[PDB]
Length: 229
Ligand SMILES: Nc1ncnc2c1ncn2[C@@H]1O[C@H](COP(=O)(O)OP(=O)(O)O)[C@@H](O)[C@H]1O
Image 1 (tube, rainbow, N blue to C red):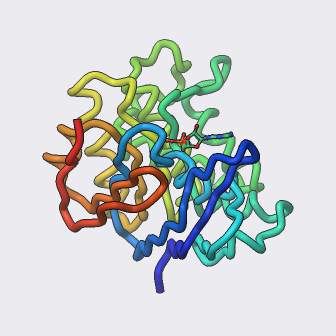
Image 2 (tube, rainbow, N blue to C red):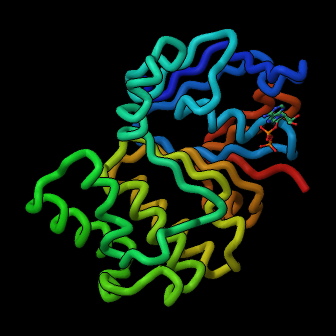
């Protein structure tokens, strides 16, 4: 079945503003989708709802098998275990080695010695930074920081990866590197939802395009174009 199912989802903030006005999106496993649209359209409310940070007021929403309306807050961490989140403002722990930044998310859930150092070296190979396993974050470039952040978000192998403007703070070439890493992640099966306003990326790296405008899905196309300024 669908890994993300959103039907007639309404999100009203307490100040009367309605960020989502009955949005319906169906995402199969392994899909790679861009979330585009003018600012204030509700892109980030859309994605924030996908890991239960935002609670919807009306409609149905299920992510990775979890009914997000009925999920108990005590279970949201279990939801996050299947739903990794990458941010614009990549922020690693500064007094921790690259290895420790990645290993923390596995130590939390109590993974044993064996799987931790194996899994950390694996994801370090994926992001191509195993040669900096013992470096701290600020000897790392910006693009390298976002790559380690992405490694952290996928260390527990989540089924879904929500990326809010992953390249928003990176120059063109480092953004291509982030997109290539996201692509290889997607090819391994991870469903990737990427909110973005980089039209070059969207138009060269053709994937599904979900365009939101004034809280409503205005466009949902295979290998679509960016379609904005
Ligand atoms: N915490 C909040 N309280 C009230 N209104 C909010 C809140 N967060 C966002 N909004 C409003 O919801 C709408 C969508 O915002 P947002 O989801 O951040 O849009 P986008 O990500 O497309 O820029 C805007 O009108 C914004 O002002």
